[PDB]
Image (cartoon, rainbow over all chains, first blue to last red):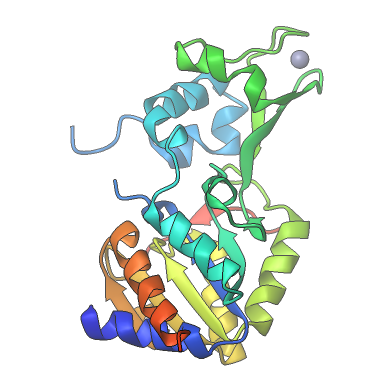
Length: 242
Length: 9
Ligand SMILES: [Zn+2]
């Protein structure tokens, strides 16, 4: 990746409007999973078994309570340098903002806000996180319903149109598009790199494993984001020195 | 109208 990292840094260095696209892989992490996200984290599943969704979240607490890693800081640095103008993410933990990124387009929402499906009461995550931490499943303090849904896009749910539009435009007008930690198997998000490819942007991908979209990237890197990204950023700094 | 789905080739 020595050569690739250098090449990736060279593209970003010259770009005028780079966009980053991140997935679950940005964070390094029986055989089959006890909780199948396509079921417990699907809208049909939630409208039928809300508690299953929360039990699943609790099992993923370490990831939900994870803090920014070097990849998030590297990405925030690239924006600060004016090289990265937008970060499109499928993630819902707000780690990009928590790391310093400003223009973050959350394709799938975030845990920040929640609504009771039955009485429509809205809540802030801060109102349930302490219960959630001790294994208590959030329940509406108004009507007692277990249908307390966070404003995150579940499988089978339409993505927020406002965010989707801006993400599409960023892809349509960027001159460099870098995928970080995304296996690109979640749609419609997975279509954004292709829109950028169609736009003529230079393509870069950093992922632990190869993807079916790999063929369209100008530079491909296999590895952990948290280890790869800072390396790139450091090579970008040198390209912007005296 | 774009619903979230997962698909692997
Ligand atoms: Zn309620």
